[PDB]
Amino acid sequence: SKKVIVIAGTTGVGKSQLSIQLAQKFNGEVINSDSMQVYKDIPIITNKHPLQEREGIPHHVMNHVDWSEEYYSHRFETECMNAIEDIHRRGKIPIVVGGTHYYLQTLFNKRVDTKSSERKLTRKQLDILESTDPDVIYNTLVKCDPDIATKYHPNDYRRVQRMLEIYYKTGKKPSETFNEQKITLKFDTLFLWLYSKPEPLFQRLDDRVDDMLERGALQEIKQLYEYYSQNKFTPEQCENGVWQVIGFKEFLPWLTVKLEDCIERMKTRTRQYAKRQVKWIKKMLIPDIKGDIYLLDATDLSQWDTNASQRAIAISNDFISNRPIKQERAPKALEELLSKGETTMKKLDDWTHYTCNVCRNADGKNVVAIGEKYWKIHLGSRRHKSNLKRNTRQADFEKWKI
Amino acid sequence: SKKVIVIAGTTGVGKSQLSIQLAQKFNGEVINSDSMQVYKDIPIITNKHPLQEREGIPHHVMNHVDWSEEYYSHRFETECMNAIEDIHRRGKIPIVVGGTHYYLQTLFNKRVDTKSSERKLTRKQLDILESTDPDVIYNTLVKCDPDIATKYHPNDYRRVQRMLEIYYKTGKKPSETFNEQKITLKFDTLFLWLYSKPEPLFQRLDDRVDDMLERGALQEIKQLYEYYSQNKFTPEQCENGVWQVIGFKEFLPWLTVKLEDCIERMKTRTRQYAKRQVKWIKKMLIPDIKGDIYLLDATDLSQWDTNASQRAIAISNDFISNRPIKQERAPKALEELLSKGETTMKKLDDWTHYTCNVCRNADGKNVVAIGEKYWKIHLGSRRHKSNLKRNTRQADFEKWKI
RNA sequence: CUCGUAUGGCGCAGUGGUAGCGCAGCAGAUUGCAAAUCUGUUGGUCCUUAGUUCGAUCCUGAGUGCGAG
RNA sequence: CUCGUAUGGCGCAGUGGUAGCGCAGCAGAUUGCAAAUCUGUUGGUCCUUAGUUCGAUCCUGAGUGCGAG
Ligand SMILES: [Mg+2]
Ligand SMILES: [Mg+2]
Ligand SMILES: [Mg+2]
Ligand SMILES: [Mg+2]
Ligand SMILES: [Zn+2]
Ligand SMILES: [Zn+2]
């Protein structure tokens, strides 16, 4: 009965705090899921409650990757899948905690294997793959497997390129692979959503940036700018590694109310990450695991012990005890959060493309709407209204000539 | 990949009526589950849509059994599995329905493989298995694997006996087998719960019995008593076959007011089945498939086309189209029906046994409560109150003699 | 006119001293029998009355409801 | 009292004919980069008021808040 407990949510609710209670209380090792904490030390700014608070619970896939390195999906795909191994073969229950919920796709069938195949990537194929022009690599995909071709935009470099590579290396179009995909989840899992109202969670996430300088956010980033030298690397790769952490790039140009230049920006970047996190849980995660998840009202921190702690244990208990849970799944307060309307409903289903002939971006290309709902939006945007007006307006230069 | 569309619900909405609407628009075979439709003709009373409005839709597992045969959970566990095969390899899709929701338990990993190891039980083992006394075969189980032993009552013949046979034939205790059981479901499934209010569904189920005589319920049962005469199946083989169908035993005295004797009884038996059906879906099915099911308000039959038909297609559609459904999963009206409280909550979790020393049934044995909740109930039942009262009295006289 | 019977929603057992069984109902169970099987439990205080009595559902008479020649 | 000056949520441009830019904010995508990357979009009656001009956000008269001796 390979069971696995997963804690999802925005930072500022107590995930790395609950993962501790649900650790010894049920014998488990906590795995990480932050495309930041994996980088050697440099805590505080990268968030990670002091070691003397992990209650001796062996964490995995975190604090080990070197600054002058890059962390990708695959990396976690194996490093995580691996930690689960050890934790399992040790009668201990894994507890995956993390903000990059994209990585949660590993805990269940959703990845495309691309290594066991030796499809000789002929020169002609690579030239198309490693092409400088985005539309030429797209049209190629449009031909072979036009299905998946529509699910993406002709400007989605990373995406279109990824799909074609799959068609080439595996031979079998990626459209079919998905049409007959397991989608099931490995190891019986228990998803816990430790959510918190936006307004408060925001006020907290900001006072968290303030009191973040006191703990030594200064030295943190300062010790970060130090590694910046003795190596040198222009923004050609100095914006994809530890560099992303909130506080580095903010004081980067401020080191070649001037304080606000970095303060307000930091507090902003934080919220953005949060907002997206929620979006991914609501539009991706939840819908995929078919609304099977348990919310935890973390809005009021003065009731966390009863609204998130106590509640968590109970739920987590029956989960491990192989006994069906009796918990309502979500407090009446945060009830709509799981409703199809606040989740799956926000998804996209109409992929039919649309092209506006009277509008185009800087790249010269005409605008490309995807979906009736959105195609109709463009046709109503000031943009379209203006181009359409000065169009029929530049035409009125004929009446005054004929 | 291979998908299936089950249709649960009592017998007073249109499960068979809708199983057709979908089986066509989405191309599929309607696998039956009702343990009554699986008998040569005799439909007018065993209920099963006539070929008239059949619209040439293929129906499996039904009408293939003869009056003289005892159908069980295995013959279905095989026939169904086979029927689905054909459908899956014929460019179609299984549209399973049925009334005996128990059998649907086969649509996933649950049962044990007590076939591979056809090990022969030593005389000593069989003697214990095929014992006449229920407590002696139970104590045996209490010893080897006391875990599963508590999940049952010392009077649960069929149950306790079945568990022991699993321990013997497989060697591995049934307690562990369940503690590490898949529980997952084979083939992506879509459960549709075509429910309807109790009051109305009852009024309908009864006018159903009335107009049931007109279609020829008389000849139906009459042609049933005819098969009775041959070999004249004594009350030995009268509860293991078509015999149990409504009308048979009901009108047995009408062939050895006198009309109500069978009328009221019939209408009653009907409701009983319905009530239990709902309970199984609410306490068993739903909880198991983790509240993943779609209700369909069939209370008002004047809105069926919109509340059950239209709605069903839509949901069914995205299901097959491999697109996550956007349907609210259950109309605000019938909302509590899926709530943990109206389902999983009704389950039993405290299995600790309890014995009353002042109470015993006809079998002589003392009462055996299972679970605090219920142990406390017994301690307050009139039964206990009386035995406890007439006890202190016929025991206080001794306290008087001296 | 002759005679028994006249108890939980219905069909029944039963004792001078304060009551039961099955059906139904409610409820739990269900990992080859599930329209089966198992388990628990809510309803009467014995048609009405006056007496017979230390006290009657069970005793006597009667008003009354059914069963018969 | 004499001069600067107020343009969408924040900061800035800008033209005689009825407006932009960066940043926020909102929305969609995501099956080896995801704190990435891609795509779409809502905000102002250009301070108030009165005039020359056919036209006023940009010219002129004061009007009001803000800043300057
Ligand atoms: Mg933390
Ligand atoms: Mg007396
Ligand atoms: Mg003044
Ligand atoms: Mg922006
Ligand atoms: Zn346009
Ligand atoms: Zn008792």
Image: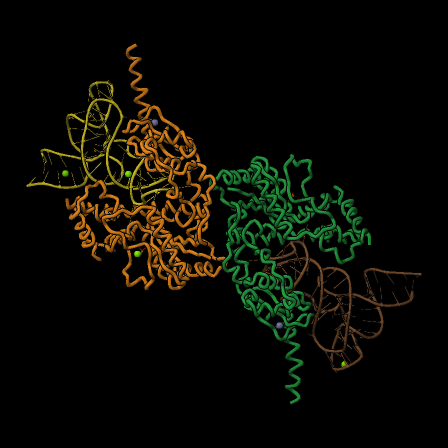
Chain colours: A orange, B green, C brown, D yellow
| Side (left or right) of A151 relative to B293 | left
Nearest to the observer: residue A293 or residue A258: A293
Q: Within the image, what quadrant is residue D3 found in? A: top left
Q: Residue furthest bottom?
A: B402
Nearest to the observer: residue A196 or residue A14: A14
Q: Where is residue C15 in the image (x, y as percent from the top left)?
A: 77, 76
Q: Within the image, what quadrant is residue A40 found in? A: bottom left
Q: Position of residue C60 (x, y in %)?
A: 84, 74
Nearest to the observer: residue D27 or residue A39: A39
**Image position of B47 with respect to B141: above or below:** above
Q: Where is residue B199 in the image (x, y as percent from the top left)?
A: 63, 50
Q: Can residue B110 be seen in this view?
A: yes
In the rendered image, the quadrant that contains the C terminus of chain A is top left
**Ligand 3 placement by image quarter:** top left
| Side (left or right) of A137 relative to A212 | right
Q: Residue furthest top?
A: A402
Going 52% across and 38% down the picture, which residue do you hit? Answer: B317
Q: Position of residue B398 (x, y in %)?
A: 65, 86
